[PDB]
């Protein structure tokens, strides 16, 4: 257990009241329950109806005539450093009803009249009569203990809330309501709460949480950030979705999609990569549409439970803070139990769990604009106060970033806390060609210093919108089938392109396919993600300085989707390029006027010691399409010839075949280093392959890593040879739809890395050819596999031994290999001589 605890709950406390007061059911004050839900075992429903909100609690009643004010006091049994207090009293005058929310007819919200209590005060101390009392909070005019002085600044009443009220130990910080620095404590044994009900002599106290430490040695402090996210410290996020089943008080940790667990996902990660990974707790459709009491209870219980399990395993955590515009801010939806977030609870999670790091937001604007901005503004402030971070994932059709800045509170929060805020793409709607513009916006936002970084969320839902079987269009298959169809190597190609643009966050869905099921690692995870991510961890991406230095043009405004065609590549929806010649092309959205953005970018460049790029409005005559190619070709020299993607960056060539789902070979012809400048490497690749090449520099050697890992889904998924049920319906006794269960069955039984007996190795044994032509050489070069992807349990090879043909009379050496997966090749004994016929590395006339 972490050092910050609810002492009121953990200790054997004594509860008392003043003379002429009656005390009833004292144990309810410190039972950890603020909601008194009764039907947890049946999904918080009795029949088809959500259970009512029924408020129970410790009742204190004045029996002194004409004097309704009461107090209740807790003796913790010893003096402890206290940091936070949470007080909740009866919220509703009478009983609240369950009425219509947002969206109308599905969302549910409590309705009724809320109580605003008066003459509320909180006093703590180390004498039982509190003659040494210190004021934590004071509203109205309750008579304090003898020896405790009236405070100068007095609070006014507030409306009681579902989560209660939160108090901290700095009276000068908003009269005790203002959240303090981690570890701001006062030592006390006795805690007294004063309250007067506006109607009558009785107050029901539903909970008094008193959070502190066992001793002063355990008191925490804010000594720096919880993590660094940058080119030298990249971060992979894996989403841990609730399976939508949970019961408050259950012994076992929350079940995740695909028979996964929080601890299980963490322990599946290779040890050397754990420091660059985080788990995102996502509530998914847990208690979806539920009214306030059920929503808040389940949001809190699910996240706390995940945090605790993570804490025991040493796993850092992000929480889903906001999706589907489901926020407690005015106008919010109830599409998710994030609707019932209590910002006091979110603060508590950072104080209680040292492994709590970040907040995640995605997919809001289809459902509402300003509510998710208002909520994100508050959560960004909280995250950054604790040295944490905030990630916002979305595709930008053109108004995503401008919507964010159009909200005054979010704009202001970004100005103060922007260094802890990260924008990552999300290519779910792959059929809209906004992938490349999104990356440009997000890179541009970072480059100019409005945000702390950028990155990627690649979603296999992208495949659903366009394709099915290999080389085929969507056809008439179920969407859960098409979800499974994406080539594994393509995920690596996407990672490579994000890396080259100085991206620092990497995340993938559908998690049960890309990371795995049943706490195992999937084929994608094992043979692509973990391999390439290890390269990214050990070979830092370009810094902001390096991006700035290589960038000759920055655009301003809402760049056209189709701008990239005939430049870096046609937007495919899959976040890949035809060439690396121009980089990502940073486009700064309208964070301010062109002049304001220009000044900001110049300041950022100056700070890095770099020449500022020129800023052009997207509408500039030079970017028209006739003149755009001329303008960009004059700024950025050609590096290689051919139709494959290639980028040379700091001595290393990065390549891929850039066809998403068309079976075409592509090539790249590279000028090689050394004394002989006519030296050439031609690479030819079939689709779904990426490559990293490093020359020795003296023209004698080179190392090549290639990866073209692709599982064939044609028979198992699309022909459906095992007769799985791919539909959106529930089957008898199931809380998960058939389509999902089928994905899980595929991953558990039919596509298993190192498949044990009775399970199938992945369908990955059909190999494809990569060829390398080296010219002009005097003698045959030497090739060998340093390391290669090993067989699954079926014994079938993932590569064949490389073959070298060398022609004496011409310079040409041809190296051929067949792979499905990764190999590290080493080529040595290269003796280049002058080649008058060497391919010219230049543009066409
Ligand atoms: C009902 C259901 O099973 N949903 C799962 C599914 O949800 C995603 C798909 O519906 C997809 C179709 O193209 O659209 C996505 O927006 C949707 O994502 C989910 O909902 C949005 C609002 C966000 O909260 C996302 O974080 C969330 O994933 O697939 C996801 C995983 O891709 C989950 O399993 C859902 O349970
Ligand atoms: Ca209680
Ligand atoms: Ca380059
Ligand atoms: Ca080198
Ligand atoms: Mg195999």
Image (cartoon, helix red, strand yellow):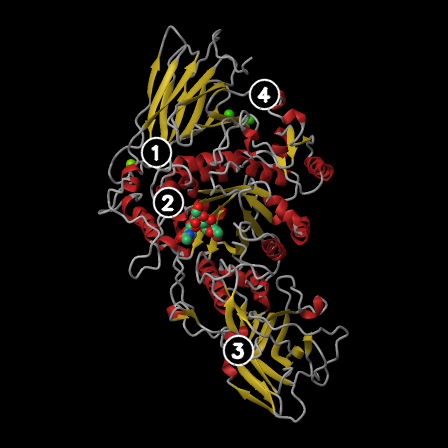
Frontmost of labels 2 and 1 is 2
Label 1 Cα neighbours within 10 Å, binned few <14 / some 14-19 / many ≥20 = some
Along the line of sight, which residue is nearer the eye, 296 or 310?
296
Q: Is residue 682 left or right of residue 150?
A: left
Q: Is residue 466 left or right of residue 547?
A: left
Where does residue 730 sit, x and y in percent of width and height?
Answer: 33, 57
Where does residue 186 sit, x and y in percent of width and height?
Answer: 64, 71
Q: Work out whether mark 2 precedes mark 4 in sequence or the reverse, and give the earlier one.
A: 2
User: Label 1, on which residue?
Assistant: 470
Residue 71 position (above or below residue 595): below
Q: Secondary structure at mark 1?
A: loop
Q: Secondary structure at mark 2?
A: helix
Q: Work out whether mark 2 precedes mark 1 in sequence or the reverse, and give the earlier one.
A: 1
Q: Quadrant of the C terminus?
A: top right
Label 4 Cα neighbours within 10 Å, binned few <14 / some 14-19 / many ≥20 = few
Along the line of sight, which residue is nearer the eye, 604 or 200?
200
Q: Work out whether mark 4 precedes mark 1 in sequence or the reverse, and give the earlier one.
A: 1
User: Label 2, on which residue?
Assistant: 479
Frontmost of labels 3 and 4 is 3
Count of numbered marks: 4
The circle drawn on residue 95 is: 3
> Looking at the image, do the residues carrying marks 4 and 1 touch, with CB atoms under 8 Å apart?
no
Cα gap from disc 3 to disc 1, whole angstroms: 59 Å
Residue 147 position (above or below residue 489): below
User: Label 4, on which residue?
Assistant: 637
Q: Which image quarter has ligand 3?
A: top right
Residue 528 position (above or below residue 204): above
> Looking at the image, do the residues carrying marks 3 and 2 touch, with CB atoms under 8 Å apart?
no
Where does residue 310 sit, x and y in percent of width and height?
Answer: 46, 58
Query: Toward which corner of the image does residue 779 lie, by quadrant?
Result: top left
Cα gap from disc 4 to disc 1, whole angstroms: 36 Å
Q: Residue furthest front?
A: 105
């Amino acid at each position: 257990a972490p050092p910050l605890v609810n002492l009121a709950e953990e200790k054997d406390v004594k509860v008392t009241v003043g003379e002429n007061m009656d005390l009833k059911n004292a144990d309810l004050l410190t039972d950890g329950d603020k909601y008194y839900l009764q039907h947890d075992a049946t999904g918080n429903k009795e029949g088809n109806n959500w259970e009512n909100y029924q408020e129970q609690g410790t009742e204190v009643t004045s029996t002194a005539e004409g004097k309704n004010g009461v107090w209740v006091q807790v003796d913790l049994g010893a003096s402890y450093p206290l940091e936070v207090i949470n007080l909740k009293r009866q919220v509703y005058d009478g009983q609240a009803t369950i009425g219509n929310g947002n969206p109308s007819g599905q969302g549910k919200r409590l309705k009724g009249t809320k109580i605003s209590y008066k003459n509320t005060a909180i006093v703590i101390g180390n004498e039982e009569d509190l003659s040494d009392g210190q004021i934590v909070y004071y509203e109205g005019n309750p008579t304090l203990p003898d020896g405790v002085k009236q405070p100068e600044n007095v609070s006014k009443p507030y409306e009681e809330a579902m989560g209660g009220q939160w108090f901290y130990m700095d009276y000068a910080n908003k009269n005790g309501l203002g959240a303090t620095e981690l570890g701001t404590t006062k030592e006390a044994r006795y805690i007294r709460v004063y309250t007067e009900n506006p109607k009558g002599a009785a107050v029901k106290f539903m909970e008094l949480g008193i959070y502190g430490y066992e001793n002063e040695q355990d008191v925490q402090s804010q000594d720096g950030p919880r993590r660094v996210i940058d080119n030298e410290h990249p971060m992979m996020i894996a989403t841990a979705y609730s399976n939508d089943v949970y019961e408050i008080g259950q012994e076992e940790g929350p079940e995740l999609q695909g028979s996964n667990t929080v601890d299980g996902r963490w322990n599946a990660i290779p040890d050397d990569l754990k420091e660059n990974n985080v788990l995102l707790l996502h509530t998914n459709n847990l208690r979806q549409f539920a009214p306030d009491h059920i929503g808040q209870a389940y949001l809190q219980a699910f996240h706390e439970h995940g945090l605790q399990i993570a804490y025991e395993q040493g796993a850092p955590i992000m929480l889903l803070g906001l999706t589907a515009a489901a926020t407690p801010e005015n106008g919010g939806t109830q599409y998710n139990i994030t609707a019932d977030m209590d910002y006091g609870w979110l603060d508590l999670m950072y104080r209680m769990y040292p492994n709590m790091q970040g907040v995640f937001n995605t997919e809001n604007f289809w459902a509402g604009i300003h509510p998710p901005c208002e909520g994100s503004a508050k959560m960004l402030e909280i995250a950054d106060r604790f040295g944490g971070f905030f990630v916002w994932s979305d595709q930008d059709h053109g108004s995503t970033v401008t919507n964010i800045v159009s909200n005054a509170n979010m704009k202001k929060a970004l100005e103060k806390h922007g260094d802890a805020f990260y924008l990552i793409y999300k290519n779910t709607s792959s059929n809209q060609p906004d992938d490349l513009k999104t990356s440009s916006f997000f890179q541009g936002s970072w480059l100019a210093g409005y945000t702390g970084g950028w990155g990627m969320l690649s979603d296999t839902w992208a495949w659903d919108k366009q394709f099915s079987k290999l080389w085929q269009g969507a056809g008439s298959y179920n969407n859960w089938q098409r979800l499974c169809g994406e080539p594994e190597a393509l995920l690596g190609m996407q990672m490579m392109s994000t890396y080259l643009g100085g991206g620092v966050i990497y995340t993938f869905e559908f998690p049960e396919i890309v990371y795995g099921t049943s706490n195992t690692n999937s084929p994608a995870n094992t043979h692509v993600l973990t391999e390439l991510f290890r390269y990214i961890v050990n070979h830092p991406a370009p810094s902001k300085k390096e991006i700035m230095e290589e960038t000759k043009a920055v655009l301003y405004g809402n760049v056209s989707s189709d701008f990239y065609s005939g430049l870096s590549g046609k937007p495919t929806g899959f976040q890949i390029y035809e060439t690396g010649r121009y980089g990502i092309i940073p486009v700064i959205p309208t964070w301010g006027t062109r002049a304001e953005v220009t000044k900001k970018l110049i300041q950022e460049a100056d700070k890095l010691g770099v020449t500022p790029p020129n800023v052009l409005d997207v509408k500039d005559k030079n970017l028209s399409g006739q003149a755009k190619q001329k303008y960009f070709k004059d700024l950025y020299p050609i590096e290689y010839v051919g139709n494959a993607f290639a980028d040379k960056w700091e001595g290393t060539w990065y390549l891929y075949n850039n066809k998403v789902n068309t079976n075409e070979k592509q090539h790249a012809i590279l000028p090689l280093e050394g004394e002989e400048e006519s030296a050439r490497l031609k690479v030819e690749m079939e689709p779904h392959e990426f490559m990293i090449m490093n020359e020795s520099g003296d023209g004698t050697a080179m190392d090549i890593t290639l990866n073209n890992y692709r599982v064939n889904k044609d028979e198992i998924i699309f022909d459906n040879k095992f007769g799985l049920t791919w539909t959106g319906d529930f089957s008898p006794g199931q809380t998960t739809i058939n389509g999902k269960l089928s994905v899980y069955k595929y991953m558990d039984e039919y596509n298993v890395v190192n498949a044990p007996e009775g399970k199938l190795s992945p369908e990955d044994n059909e190999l494809r050819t990569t060829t390398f032509e080296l010219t002009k050489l005097a003698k045959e070069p030497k090739v060998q596999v340093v390391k290669g992807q090993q067989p699954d349990t079926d014994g079938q090879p993932q590569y064949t031994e490389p073959k070298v043909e060398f022609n004496e009379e011409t310079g040409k050496a041809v190296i051929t290999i067949q792979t499905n997966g990764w190999v590290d090749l080493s080529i040595t004994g290269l003796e280049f001589v002058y080649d008058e016929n060497a391919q010219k590395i230049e543009d066409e006339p």
